[PDB]
Amino acid sequence: KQVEIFTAGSALGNPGPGGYGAILRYRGREKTFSAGYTRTTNNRMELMAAIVALEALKEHAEVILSTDSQYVRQGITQWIHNWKKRGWKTADKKPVKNVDLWQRLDAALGQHQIKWEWVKGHAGHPENERADELARAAAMNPTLEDTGYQVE
Image (cartoon, rainbow, N blue to C red; front, side):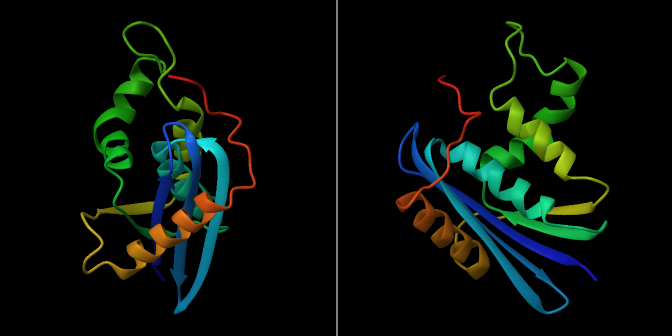
């Protein structure tokens, strides 16, 4: 009864139009999520894709979450536990960049048992490539405001 999730984010500027793609497969069937934002960043969309996919889970699950985001990998495996120790502030006492989405992602993890698959490259990873096609299509026709995006 494992859930497989494949996520990607894309943005056309720093900040610029951006979007996310997420694919969820469970007991043979698939569900897809994609939305575009008018002013955002690649890293925020990479986070948003994982958030939206995980928030769609209505029951505690065993999840295999595949993403090619280096940013998500570093947050999950290197930074988040230290950020929590420090009250979500850097050494200069400013809030961590994208703290709104990191905290929302941490809540979206819920009680799921997640095995993260950090993929490098689209070759041999068709669902990741498709998630990226969804993110890019959403970035080309954005409808939402990424209200939490802040300069710098």
